[PDB]
Amino acid sequence: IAWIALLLLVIFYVFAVMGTKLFAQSFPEWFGTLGASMYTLFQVMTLESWSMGIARPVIEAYPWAWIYFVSFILVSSFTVLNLFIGIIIESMQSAGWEAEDAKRIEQEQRAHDERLEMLQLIRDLSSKVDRLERRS
Amino acid sequence: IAWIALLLLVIFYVFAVMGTKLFAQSFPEWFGTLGASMYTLFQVMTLESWSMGIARPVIEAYPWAWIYFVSFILVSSFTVLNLFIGIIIESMQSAGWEAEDAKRIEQEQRAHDERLEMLQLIRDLSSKVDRLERRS
Amino acid sequence: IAWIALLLLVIFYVFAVMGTKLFAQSFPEWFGTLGASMYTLFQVMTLESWSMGIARPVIEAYPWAWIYFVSFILVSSFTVLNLFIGIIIESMQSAGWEAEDAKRIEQEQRAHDERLEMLQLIRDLSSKVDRLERRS
Amino acid sequence: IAWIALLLLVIFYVFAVMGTKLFAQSFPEWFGTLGASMYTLFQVMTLESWSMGIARPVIEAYPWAWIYFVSFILVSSFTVLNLFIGIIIESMQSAGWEAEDAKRIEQEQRAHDERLEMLQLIRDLSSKVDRLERRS
Image (cartoon, rainbow over all chains, first blue to last red; front, side):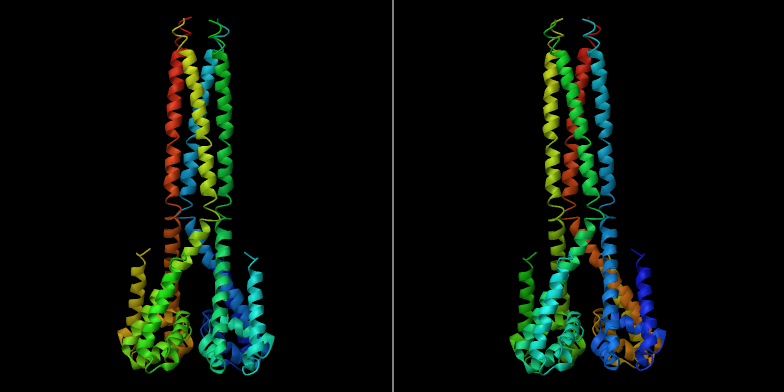
């Protein structure tokens, strides 16, 4: 799960230098610094005035910015979906299906100890009986 | 799961030509092209200034646009809910309940091999014994 | 699950007449009609300019409107959470844990048919043997 | 699950007095009272004009407010994720994996009653047979 939290903080990083490279020119409030894009893209990630506030006016200057915003939201919120699910799995198979996946791993092999002793008891009886057809 | 990703990209398409047909007239910034609606509806799908920015002013010109926006959000975000769930199911029954659904499919039939051999051993003993009530 | 889709469409209704009763006076664009509140509250439920657009200006006229908006969002989005979960449960215990809850209900009782026949075979052997201690 | 609903309503509280302490000075509409921050932070938690509306203008006065907003959203929406998951777990292991975790706790021990009676029957037979090699 936390092996993707690295990936997310890489995409966040990659796209922050992208926007600083592109829009630092004409949108210096949103993309002037690296640290200003780190904020803007967080705001863009949270989908609060992402388009009407940021994307639309940025797309007005460069139409090659349309994809930068769309692709960012697509990849960003998608690797959160992979991350949100990475907690539902690691949580529902840890508190429920990791304790049951061992209690039924034990209750199954606690009757292989029952069946395989009982088997021996029947063989110890096949030995006592088949030695009495050779004795009568 | 990805059999609905086609459906979503059909609803996205269907509604994009709808808005271009309707609003290309008076809202050319948002619905002028097919490609402008493809953007606007993505923005409307992400619920960022969807109403106050897009729907409200569009509903001011045509009140028959109220339903276009509401219905779009309802169907769109609903087939994402069907898609979001389509990953939680295909993920929690693949990494947990597809490996366990085979290890308990094997552990169950590894004792039918135990019970049905043991049965034979008892019949081989019923054969040795019921041939000794006919021998005494 | 769909037994709460009724409840949600009741809260939606209840609060729509509430807002039309209260704010139809001074906010006639948002709450003038029943059908205008049905839209506004849908927009409020989707959390798009819910506060800065609707609540804040409505709270400026009446401070007894603060709770109307907060309580609405709390109850509304909470019975969606009960509804969103009502599909995750009804879907993950239907496609996975309703077919397995019957295949293991059958595989369990397919060996009670094995154990209880084998038992009889041993009793049919206790009958053949304990009638040979009375015969020797 | 509801043991974190207390924690959330503590973070909500902690950060509300924080913002009233800091921003009551120059942003009295958003942070003037304790009760105004309780609203603003709810609006900030719902990510509706959180940055462009609240954070950005507040960051314009104090750049030491950037972290207050980011950290709030991070911790707040994260302990909702822990809370949202705390219902998926407590619901999917209660309606499905708490009734099955008892029906298979009973079906397992209803055949230990079978195997351990059958064992006795074989021993009662080893007693009858091994007393007939000492009798012939």
